[PDB]
Length: 48
Length: 93
Length: 93
Length: 394
Image (cartoon, rainbow over all chains, first blue to last red; front, side):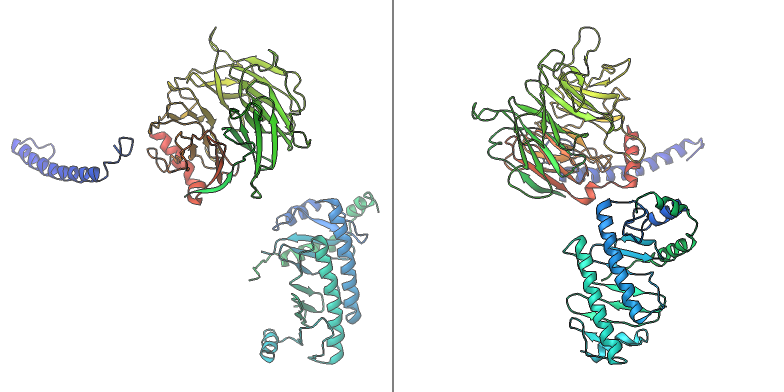
């Protein structure tokens, strides 16, 4: 989508956005999993 | 030029300028510790003269300009022309 | 081995003559004739003893493990360690 | 014969054959062939002179990188035993005892090598008198002692050093009172130049740390006990404190300027070590500390740059661990960090002038010599560019 004026174009853009956010939430799950498995050491710096 | 020879010889590995020893056993040029170089210069003159006699024993038409005095610590490049004995301290590698 | 060593040391450059000298000078082996081999090898032994003294003068633990003379008419090679004194007669080139 | 006719014979023009011979032998002789991690490196712990007697300061000799001076100050086990002992320990050979032993009547607590004299040791003591030690003499007593006058230092002194060229030296020493003074290394009977450091009217400086920038001697940085770092000019119209720095709320326990050269300058940068584990990679040009590395419950006691690495530096900690921060590698975790046995309060760290080995102090007097891995010790050509990029990050 670009300079398109149609609001149905906006809805298609919204579908693209929810797919984008599906990948975004996949990234969130990845980074949170990498988070918790690296946690539990202590509070300082790289630990927390 | 003397300075050109200085800079050309100092380019060689482990060589501090150029030092030349005359027939009197003293180095005509000063580049390192004087007493050690003078005594070892008398020594090189002694054994190069004896090598000259040795070669003239069977080869009375040969001239000496090349000798590879190398040990496990350094190589010594002694080369006499007629009077000016060229000596170079050089690492074996 | 003996013969194989002499053959491989000779054929590498077509050397005019080499004998094995495992003793302190005075070798009985010959490669072209007895005198020019034996007397010259004894003279080489004397001169390399003097050279060993020379290299020990600067520092006694030094020893001469390699020696070559390349003059206008001949090339002489010797690599002494404790008694293995080599002889090579060759053209200067 | 003598060395005069040789000059004319050299100026004599029969040397064409000699030059040809030299050129030929050199060109023929040109060809040359052949004929055929953090680690505890060493230890240094006296027993007669190091029963308790915590370490105070260390140094390496520029002329003899194999030599290190130790300084043990406190004497509490016995009033009768020596109060201040200075021990020099050699690197070339391993011995159970220091190579030479020195005593001062007072408690020696700051010491350094002498640059002009390669056989002299100078140290600062608790009384505030500058203490000399000529290694030529066989006496353990100090050779030359500065008077306890108001002109000289009368308060405890922490920063003593000799700087300048070989033909121009000045013994810069500053005490806790805030007074600076210079001396000639051969004459210390009188202060050759001295004035007390003072900021805006009626504000003294509780000096406890100092470090000259590499090369510069006219200006420098001073670490104060009040946790506020200052830059001072050694000599000039503006001789005195020239910079107010917020620093940290904890007293400064060490300071050092950049100790690397070869690429883009970083000497304006400096490292300060506070009392609350707050080291500040930071430049004199800026007023805000660039970074404030924080961790642990304990705190630093000294911080020293790498003499060769423009990014690595060492840190002290109170529970016995020594950490390395290579900023290019990372800025959040120490690049290398190990703990010495017995969890003692380390007090001094001094990088070897070569930069290949690091010494550390101790709370019991046992000097631990630490060696580092090659990959972590030597920097690269791209190391300087990476350091510049990391500094440009914020």
